[PDB]
Amino acid sequence: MRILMVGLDGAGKTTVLYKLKLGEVITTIPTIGFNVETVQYKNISFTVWDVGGQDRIRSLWRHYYRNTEGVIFVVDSNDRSRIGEAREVMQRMLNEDELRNAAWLVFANKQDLPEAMSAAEITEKLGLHSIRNRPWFIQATCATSGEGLYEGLEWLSNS
Amino acid sequence: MDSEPPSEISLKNDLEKGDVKSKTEALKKVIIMILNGEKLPGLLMTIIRFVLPLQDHTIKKLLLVFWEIVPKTTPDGRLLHEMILVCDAYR
């Protein structure tokens, strides 16, 4: 299974990936580029493309769209200023023809932080209810603990 | 591929295949058809996707090659930006 994981910078995309691959919480640098890794979960081998979220790189995601079976969209639940921006990025991503049938999994992340928005709140802000054309799911996660990560891999594998 | 102007559908297939040699050969086949002067933009997203960050020189060199002879014309996988897919991860 081919997976594209994106989201704004600092959402926690690489932390998520290497928690999944190494069971370890690594010390990230901003990703100017991608990381690509293969992860085994329950007889599925997920090839995850973690593509950096800062602006220059954001402009490049479209090259990773093609062949994508599922999309992990990571959100920093503690950052309320950038939630609209996330909504804007994700909405036009939903309009992409190469992403047309891909399974849509939102991770509301850093759920560990006291003022993190809830997954329900995030669902309203991102406009997730309005997707009728394909599968979507939202999952509260904490990438450092590992909470919600495998519930994500589970949902994804049931595409 | 000496000069074969309709072969762009096969090149897309050959461009990502999970085999590095095939990808290199494909990108090479694109170069030779452009230099003669033949069809090339269909491929762009495929071309750009494997190679981008890597320090692995041969594909990078190949992509680097294709950016001095047609970068401006091709726009499927590049479009128009300041830090295009010609140079963003080529920093």
Image (cartoon, coloured by chain):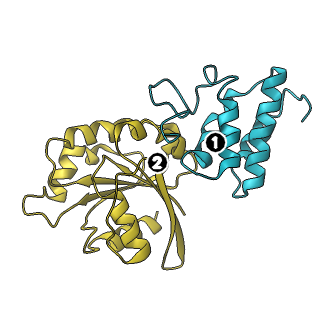
Chain colours: A yellow, B cyan
* Left or right, B87 with reference to B25: left
The answer to whether residue B43 shows anywhere in this view is no
What is the crowding at mark 2: few (fewer than 14 residues within 10 Å), some, or many (at least 20)? many
Q: Is residue A129 toward the left or the right of residue A56 in the image? A: left
Residue type, mark 2 in image: Gly
Residue A24 location in percent, x, y? 35, 76
- Expressed as whole percent of the image width and height from the top left, the position of residue B14 reads 76, 47
Q: Is residue A116 visible?
A: yes
Q: Residue at x 35, y 37 (%)?
A: A55
How far, Cα to Cα, is label 1 from label 2?
Answer: 16 Å
Q: Residue at x 80, y 45 (%)?
A: B25
Does A91 sit above or below residue A108? above
Foreground disc of the pair 1, 2? 2
Q: Nearer the viewer, residue B39 or A106?
A: B39
Secondary element under disc 2, as helix, strand or loop, is: loop
Residue tagged 1: B46
Q: Residue at x 28, y 67 (%)?
A: A143
Q: Chain of mark 1?
A: B
Name the quadrant of the N terminus of chain A: bottom right
Which residue is at the front of the view, B48 or A133?
B48
Point 25% across, 43% down: residue: A127
Which residue is disc 2 drawn over? A33
Tell me if residue B51 comes above or below residue B32 in the rendering.
below
Query: Which amino acid does the dot numbered 1 rest on?
Result: Thr
